[PDB]
């Protein structure tokens, strides 16, 4: 009995491996992973064995590897007794005998082609699968990886990495103490909601995304998918200013990486264009809702209709004049807001401009804050600022991190937008100031789920995540308000089908 | 071979158990815990065995317990063969035979007096200890619990509970997968700081408080003591506006409970009086530094000296005229700040008053925000607001929770004060509005440690924590600015000796 694992790097969707006798990508870090994973020996005078087909043996140059015995599955190659680091077997079934004897071989790894992968799974010899998912699908394959059978379960999913603008993950598939559990549960019976642990229950398998991945939830999309589960388990049914009631908890956070990936949800086709047009709308200082409607973006029409505006006591306002919201408080703080058609160039504290000047001249400064809560002009807003405070931080490696506090997040409609919106905003500040994107942390107050999103959000938790895409700018801009949608390149985004959710006006 | 545990409820410091033949406290939940912990059987047709001395057998009334065999250790009591749920042995050594030959007994529990506790440890019969630490020391004992030998290590420590204004914990003392670890480490060698996991390394045992408690870090003081450990492991040496450099990370949070306890650090004698006088100073709208100096509180002298004020370009300011800091922005927002001795009654948005009126009339409201960042009047401040935004939330149980975002935390000098300040403020808002204290969450930006605190904070991590104290008000106040230091009763606070740290002016 010895561990027999599979090492493979396939595409994210079609699961393709190699084209015309060679690989369709050149990722250096992946090959280094193959080296480290196949040289993992626990004893000293022992070496691992790698199994591959002839066409794979040909593709690697017919040369042995460092302290690894190469096993070739060929019906034509002669068993050369000269080379001890390369052995040839006539078939895969006969080749699996270095487990009942040959103690020298510690572990066994299967890394051949489709012909060897398919026969290794159908014969039930595989105990573990090391999968490297590459985000490449607009190309052509000729050799694919067989679909993983239901007997294997995902146990680990790494963070999204990047190499030459190509995103890739690392997953593990396994074939599927007691003294504290019998005490915390007893204290949970004595104290009900007196014990704070009962107020934050661990979600059950029915709302936990990919529950087989227990200890290896490293993909930072789980920071969002586990928040949905945490709301369904502990969310309190509550009313609000709209007719749609919510399930809300208080005090949650999400952490994201922006160096090797771009935090854009893959479990739902997020409209990335609508997020950008809203962000550049904020950066320009514009509070005219029609400008977004004139760009085929209808996300501020509900909160800017004639019925809604007169309902909240703003009948004196034009159709889509939202008012001093983010975008007016960013560029003009404490400015006498008249209408949307007015000229505020020069009035108000330009927080965004001073923020850039502070990030360049004083990086070690701790007060790189951008606020949006102005109590003096709240009754004039069509809607109070949801994402309020935002703090930025420069590391010693010229990286730019971002922290956001959100008073209430509409998980399903507002959180996926706010994740990408401030991720793009951080990258824009990083380019203009000359830094690199770092980490993104979002601190949430009233994390709620509207009751008409339960059917859709329950579907999102059923979809296993995919690696994050890459976001690259097409040109360096002079100022900051010069970005255009054409200057944005989204690389390797293959999400799940979009699910429609209605906005609670 | 079967488990032989010890169940005991001793004092926090002297470890006292019982006085004049009875217990020195009446905690109903503790007895309920003793019942549930001794009725934990896995086999149905099997019963546990409880061992106690004669003087303890007398204290419980000489009556058996529900489906538990009581073993009495007495040299005078006759072995009554009539009662099958009570058996008498002449000594403790002879009484322990129901493990090698008696299958009927599943588990063994030792819960006698000092005579049985000391003999159970000195003879090395104990495999596990269930300790209930009660915060009572101003009384008199007569029977104590033996000091835990070095062979036992803490494995679990529950949250601080409360019963009749008495805090108590629950601890466990034990006698002192593998496939994913060998993959995340490999990815940590390939990618250096490219992998986000390496930027947030798990602290080492040498800076981890009570490293034996791995899975049972439920005491919410660990939310602060593990933040110190996380800074020492991953903190980047950085400069700032003062001569003292720091070790800072970005994006950390802490969680606290205010229902059954009061988040006041026990690893250091925190000056609670100075925290209150600062908090009530904010509520009144006062920005005069001398008023705290006239109350034997010298925490704003460094940032309010004649030398410091002229160094930051405010030489035209009086001695301790701090300016519009928190405390002016709370009660008077966007008010024309003149001097410290002015009458701003009527000018500026009274955020605190509107907050109280909103918490009463509209609890389900999501915009219970109290901000302190006013970019229009930042150059007038002697020091920008460190703790900026604060959001409040009413649960369905008429409880008041609080979320805070802090721009920079001086861990060791500023964090312990800010924890209690917003904890007391939440209780003040809860009483005036008619709610109960709930949860407290603090969201941190630049979590740093000044380099002159390393010797002291490394000492703070060496002392194992103690249960939180209780904070109760002595009277109900009419408004909110009527609180006085005499109206506060701190119950059960037994911290470690105070350690002096210098403020980076
Ligand atoms: N992304 C990845 O992880 C990997 C990708 N690849 C790619 O896949 C491609 C190659 O794979 P593939 O085309 O499927 O060819 P294979 O690598 O699977 O090799 C197949 C050959 O092995 C022999 N063989 C296979 N099955 C048997 C059997 N049951 N009994 C006896 N002999 C057998 C035959 O050779 P013979 O003629 O001697 O009988 C057969 O032609 C390449 O492009 C390569 O780059 C390869 C490895 C890994
Ligand atoms: N806080 C807690 O968890 C608990 C507290 N207590 C408190 O502790 C106090 C009582 O405990 P304590 O004073 O120590 O007395 P004990 O409960 O330990 O009982 C001692 C008696 O057991 C017999 N005994 C003790 N040692 C031996 C021995 N080595 N060999 C043979 N017989 C022995 C003797 O009985 P004999 O007269 O026959 O010689 C002795 O009088 C009470 O206040 C009680 O309430 C008790 C249990 C739990
Ligand atoms: C069989 N094969 C195809 C191939 C390519 N990429 C993969 N990637 C993964 N994740 N898994 C595989 N099984 C895999 N297989 C191989 C095997 C080894 C080398 C190789 O050159 N290995 C060097 C790697 C050199 C390096 O460190 O850069 C070694 O030292 O083992 C290339 C292709
Ligand atoms: C020997 N003794 C003293 C006593 C009191 N408190 C303790 N508390 C702790 N944590 N550990 C002990 N060993 C302990 N012992 C006892 C033992 C049982 C009961 C008792 O009444 N038990 C009932 C409990 C009734 C209830 O649910 O409140 C039971 O069903 O077990 C009281 C005192
Ligand atoms: N209650 C409440 N009030 C709010 N006011 C303003 C907002 C922001 C916002 C308003 C609307 C949306 C929205 O429809 N997203 C979306 C989601 C999935 C698929 C497609 C789309 C848009 C369609 C497209 O591609 O055009 C997103 C964000 C907001 C909110 O989210 N909730
Ligand atoms: N850099 C920086 N600047 C700041 N300006 C204003 C503050 C607030 C503050 C200033 C000082 C303290 C302080 O000495 N605490 C303390 C800690 C442990 C033991 C005893 C004490 C006081 C002794 C006693 O009062 O009994 C706390 C809080 C602040 C800060 O914390 N850091
Ligand atoms: O950027 C946004 N992010 C967001 O989460 N919302 C959602 C949060 C909440 O569901 C609603 C605001 O309702 P309320 O003002 O009562 O908090 O809008 C709206 C935005 F514009
Ligand atoms: O309530 C407070 N909390 C706090 O953490 N500081 C410390 C944090 C840091 O040491 C300093 C902030 O100065 P600056 O952020 O301008 O560097 O004050 C000060 C307070 F008054």
Image (cartoon, coloured by chain):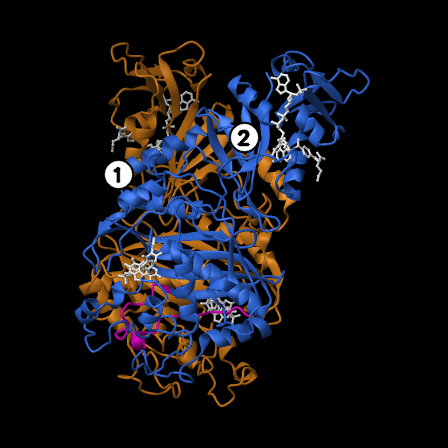
Chain colours: A blue, B orange
Q: Is mark 1 within 8 Å of ligand 4?
A: yes
Local crowd at mark 2 within 10 Å, few (<14), some, or many (≥20)? Answer: many
Residue B243's spot in the image, x, y percent? Answer: 62, 71
Quadrant showing the C terminus of chain A: bottom left
Q: Is residue A281 left or right of residue B230?
A: left
Q: Chain of mark 1?
A: B
Residue B423's spot in the image, x, y percent? Answer: 35, 60
Res. B156 image quadrant:
top left
State whether residue B217 appears in this view. Answer: yes
Q: Nearer the viewer, residue A55 or A402?
A: A55
Q: Is residue B171 above or below residue B92?
A: below
Res. A185 image quadrant:
top left
Residue A86's spot in the image, x, y percent? Answer: 75, 22
Q: Is residue B441 left or right of residue B503?
A: left
Check disc 2 and report its element: helix, strand or loop: loop
Q: CA distance from mark 1 to mark 2?
A: 62 Å
Query: Circle 2 is placed at which residue position?
Result: A145
Residue B28's disc is 1
Contact between labelled residues 2 and 1, with CB atoms less than 8 Å apart: no
Question: Furthest-bottom residue in view?
Answer: B316
Q: Nearer the viewer, residue A366 or B81?
A: A366
Q: Is mark 2 within 8 Å of ligand 1?
A: yes
State which image quarter holds ligand 1: top right
Q: Main secondary structure of the magenta part?
A: loop
Viewer-nearest of discs 1 and 2: 2
Residue B15's spot in the image, x, y percent? Answer: 42, 40
Q: Is residue B456 above or below residue B182?
A: below
State whether residue B271 appears in this view. Answer: no
Q: Residue at x 44, y 50 (%)?
A: B221
Res. A225 image quadrant:
top left
Q: Nearer the viewer, residue A470 or B391?
A: A470
Residue extent of the magenta highlight: A365-387
């Amino acid at each position: 009995e010895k561990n027999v694992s599979i090492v493979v790097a396939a595409s994210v969707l079609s699961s393709g491996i190699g084209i015309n006798g060679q690989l369709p990508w050149s990722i250096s870090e992946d090959l280094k992973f193959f080296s480290k994973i196949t040289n993992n020996k626990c004893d000293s005078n022992k070496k691992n064995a790698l199994i591959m087909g002839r066409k794979t043996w040909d593709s690697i140059g017919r040369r042995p590897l460092k302290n690894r015995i190469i096993v070739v599955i060929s019906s034509s190659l002669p068993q050369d007794e000269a080379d001890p680091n390369v052995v040839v077997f006539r078939n895969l079934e006969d080749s699996i005998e270095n487990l009942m004897n040959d103690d020298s071989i510690e572990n066994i790894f299967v890394c051949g082609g489709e012909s060897i992968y398919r026969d290794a799974l159908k014969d039930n010899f595989v105990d573990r699968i090391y999968l490297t998912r590459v985000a490449l699908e607009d190309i052509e394959f000729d050799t694919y990886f067989p679909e993983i059978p239901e007997t294997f379960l995902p146990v680990y999913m790494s963070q999204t990495f990047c190499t030459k603008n190509i995103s890739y993950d690392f997953m593990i598939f396994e074939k599927q103490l007691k003294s504290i559990d019998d005490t915390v549960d007893l204290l949970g019976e004595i104290f009900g909601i007196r014990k704070m642990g009962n107020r934050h229950k661990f979600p059950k398998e029915e709302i936990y995304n990919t529950p087989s991945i227990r200890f290896g939830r490293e993909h930072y999309e789980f920071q969002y998918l586990d928040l949905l589960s945490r709301v369904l388990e502990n969310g309190a049914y509550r009313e609000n200013r709209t007719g749609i009631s919510t399930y809300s908890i208080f005090g949650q956070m999400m952490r994201f990486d922006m160096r090797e990936s771009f935090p854009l949800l893959t479990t739902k086709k997020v409209a990335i264009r609508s997020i950008f047009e809203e962000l550049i709308w904020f950066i320009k200082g514009d509070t005219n809702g029609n400008h977004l409607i004139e760009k085929k973006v209808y996300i501020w029409s509900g909160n800017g209709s004639k019925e809604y505006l007169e309902r909240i006591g703003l009948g004196h306002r034009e159709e889509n004049d939202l008012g001093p919201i983010y975008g007016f408080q960013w560029r003009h703080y404490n400015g006498e807001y008249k209408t949307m058609h007015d000229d505020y160039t020069g009035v108000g504290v330009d927080q965004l401009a001073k923020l850039i000047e502070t990030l360049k001249n004083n990086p070690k400064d701790r007060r790189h804050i951008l606020t949006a809560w102005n109590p003096s002009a709240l009754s004039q807003m069509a809607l109070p600022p949801c994402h309020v405070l935002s703090q930025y931080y420069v590391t010693n490696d010229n990286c730019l991190s971002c922290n956001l506090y959100q008073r209430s997040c509409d998980l399903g409609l507002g959180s996926p937008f706010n994740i990408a919106s401030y991720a793009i905003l951080t990258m824009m500040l990083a380019q203009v100031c000359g830094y690199e994107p770092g980490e993104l942390a979002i601190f949430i107050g009233d994390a709620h789920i509207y009751e008409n999103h339960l059917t859709q959000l329950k579907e999102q938790l059923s979809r296993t995540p995919r690696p994050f895409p890459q976001l690259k700018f097409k040109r360096k801009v002079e100022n900051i308000e010069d970005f255009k949608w054409e200057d944005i390149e989204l690389i390797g985004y293959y999400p799940y089908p979009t699910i429609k959710m209605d906005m609670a006006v």
